[PDB]
Amino acid sequence: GSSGSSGQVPKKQTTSKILVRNIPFQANQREIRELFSTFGELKTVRLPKKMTGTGAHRGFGFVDFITKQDAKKAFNALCHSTHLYGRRLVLEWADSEVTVQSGPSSG
C-alpha cells in the first residue's frame, strides 16, 4: 500500500521518469536501452555497473524518454506485463522530492 498522491499545484509538464525495478542479473544497460527505445527515443538509459565490492548489478534501472507521451505509452506498454529472463519486471514512476525555490527565474 503505497499511496503518495500529494504536492503543491500540478505543473504543466509531468514528471517523466520510468524506473524499472526487479531487473534480472542477466539484464544489462543495452538490454533495457533498446527494450524501451523500441517504443521511442530515450533521453538516457542509466544502469548500475559492478563496482569493487559485493553485488554487481542491482535490480533497478532508470529510463528517460524524450517526451511525456513516449514515456506514457512505453511505461504502460511494459508495466502491464514484462517478463525478462523468467522475471516479471516492475515499472514505476520514480518518486521525486518537493523542493521550493527562493529566487525567481530571470529569463
Image: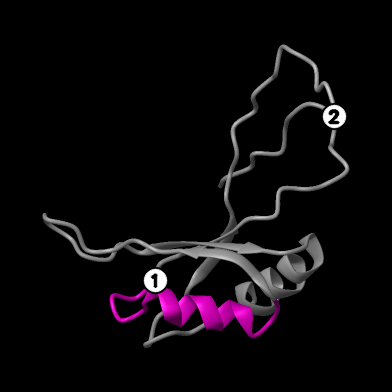
- Residue with the mark numbered 1: 23
Left or right of 69, for residue 88:
left
Q: Going by the picture, which residue comes out furthest to the front?
A: 107
Where is the C terminus found, in terms of image quarters?
Answer: top right
Range shown magenta? 23-40
Q: Does residue 29 belong to the magenta stretch?
A: yes
N-terminal label among 2 and 1:
2
Depth order, front residue of 76/43: 43
| Residue pictured at 88% horizontal, 43% vertical | 12
Disc 2 element: loop
Residue 72: where, in percent of width, then height? Answer: 75, 66
Identity of the residue furthest to the left in this view: 53
Q: At which x and y percent is residue 26?
A: 30, 81
Q: Quadrant of residue 50?
A: bottom left
Whether residue 105 is visible here, answered yes or no, is yes
Percent from the top left, x then y, of residue 62?
A: 50, 60
Query: Quick check: 34 above or below 74?
Result: below
Could you tell me which residue is drawn at 36 percent across and 77 percent down? 28
Judge by depth and name the residue closer to the eye, 4 or 92: 92
**Residue 46 versus residue 106 in the image, above or below:** below
Q: Residue furthest top?
A: 102
Badge 1 crowding class, 10 Å Cα cut-off, few under 14, some 14 to 19, many 20 or more, is many
Query: In this view of the protein, which residue sits in the foreground, 72 or 42?
Result: 42
Q: Residue at x 64, y 24 (%)?
A: 99
Q: Is 51 situated left or right of 70 in this image? A: left
Quadrant of residue 54 within the rendered picture:
bottom left
SS class of the residue under badge 1?
A: loop
> Circle 2 sits on which residue?
9
Identity, as a three-letter code, of the amino acid under mark 2? Val
Q: Position of residue 84 (x, y in %)?
A: 43, 85
Q: CA distance from mark 2 to mark 1?
A: 34 Å
What is the three-letter code of the residue carrying label 1?
Ile
